[PDB]
Structure formats: structure tokens, C-alpha cells
Image (tube, coloured by chain):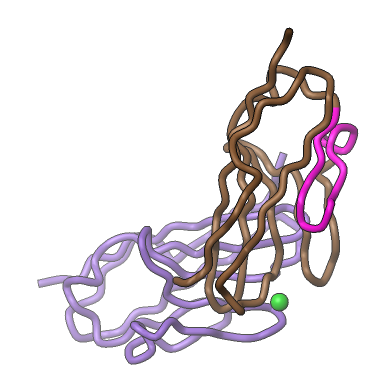
Chain colours: A purple, B brown
Amino acid sequence: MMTGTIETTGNISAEKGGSIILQCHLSSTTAQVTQVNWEQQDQLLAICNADLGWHISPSFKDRVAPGPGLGLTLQSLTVNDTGEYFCIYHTYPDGTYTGRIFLEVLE
Amino acid sequence: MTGTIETTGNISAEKGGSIILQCHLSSTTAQVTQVNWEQQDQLLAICNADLGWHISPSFKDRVAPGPGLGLTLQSLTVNDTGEYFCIYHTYPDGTYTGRIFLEVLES
Ligand SMILES: [Cl-]
């Protein structure tokens, strides 16, 4: 019933120390994007709210720049950064769409 | 981090009658972007701070918005039995979820 789909930047590799762009895109729906959250299973990274702008959560402020667009740029990568990241689009009237990216930080 | 959700709890109600599902978000000053009413599988309604109520079309006959941020179900059937979720999408806090289990009865 819900027609939106999400593309993402895929399952990726960067190396210890570097940077990476996390990005998604919502296709195939005319619904309004009211907010995008970036999260892990257990943690919030950042929110773009259509009305209010970007908020980066304090534990990531140091090493995360908003954008480009609705994406996120991770800096100073460590091994601990390995795992799943999620771009969560909150929309009206369709509701929540979620894309997934797996990151692996290399030895 | 700081918010908590009260709900109307776990409920029994009678085949054919009506019920109010309600949640309240406390202990956070964060702005509520919208509140989704969902089952595990499906969206029932969204109340969005800018756009107002959307009642999802397949539920329009049996779900009336309100009171406030809650939902009223009418003409319950045994299928209506299950989990309902009130999912607050907020800035800068993120998502808080309240749970309500509905068990619908004969006699
Ligand atoms: Cl807002």
C-alpha cells in the first residue's frame, strides 16, 4: 500500500582515521518529509527537522558534520564505528520509511 | 533521553463498542513534530503539528481522531485484538514509543 522506497549509499568501507558520507533518498512518494533521523540500533546521531534544522547529539558533535543534504558526514573513524546506521524518514501522510547502511572500518 | 510516556494501559473492551486510546509525553520540553498511531503492521493515523490529522483511508470508517492526540476506535471486532503504539517523533529528542495492548471480548 505504501509506495515510497529508499536508496542509500550501500554497504561500505572506509579506513581508520578517515571520513565518509552517509546519505539516503526517498523515491516514489509525493508525501511530505517532516523529519529525518540518523540513528544506530541503540543511539541517536542527528535529526533534520523541516521546520527547525539540524541537531547533532552531543556525543557525536565532535566528529560529524550535517550534510550534504539530508545525509551525514562522519569524521575521524574508529573501529568502534563498525555496524549498522539507519536513515529514518518521517513523512505525512505515509508515515515512517527506513533505509539501512552497513559500515565496516578497516585494519 | 529524559521523556516518558503514559498510556491508557492494557484494556479489555466488548465486541461492537468503542474505545479511546491515548498517550501523554512528559518530562521533556522537546517539540513534537507528529504523533503516529500504528499497529505492528500498519499505520492508523498521524497527528502532525503543522498539517493536522491524517486518518489512513482503510481505517476511516472505524477510527475517529481525538480526543487530543489520541484515537477513538468504534465497532470493535476480535481482529482488532493486539498491540497499538503511539509513536512521538520529536525534536531534538527523537522518538518515544508508548505501548497499549487491546483485547476484545464476547459474552
Ligand atoms: Cl516541528
Task: Tell me residue B23's x, y (percent).
Answer: 67, 53
Q: How many marks?
A: 0
Left/right placement of residue B3 relative to residue B44 reads: left
Task: Tell me residue A43's x, y (percent).
Answer: 38, 67
Question: Which residue is at 72% across, 43% downward?
Answer: B21
The answer to whether A58 is drawn above or below residue A3 in the figure is below
Q: Residue furthest right?
A: B61
- Give the quadrant of residue A97: bottom right
Q: In this orientation, which residue lies closer to the viewer: B96 or B17? A: B17
- Give the quadrant of residue B63: top right
Q: Residue furthest top?
A: B107
Q: Quadrant of ligand 1?
A: bottom right
Image: magenta residue range? B58-74
Question: Which residue is at 31% across, 86% downward?
Answer: A75
The answer to whether A41 is drawn above or below residue A79 in the figure is above
If the image is split into quadrants, where does the C terminus of chain A sit?
bottom left
If the image is split into quadrants, where does the N terminus of chain A sit?
top right
Question: Which residue is at 58% across, 66% downward?
Answer: A25
Left/right placement of residue B15 relative to residue B81 reads: right
Magenta-span inclusion, residue A61:
no
Question: Which residue is at 59% across, 35% downward?
Answer: B10
- Give the quadrant of residue B87: bottom right
Task: Tell me residue A33's x, y (percent).
Answer: 70, 67
Task: Tell me residue B46's x, y (percent).
Answer: 75, 54
The answer to whether A51 is drawn above or below residue A106 in the figure is below
Q: In this orientation, which residue lies closer to the viewer: B106 or A46? A: B106
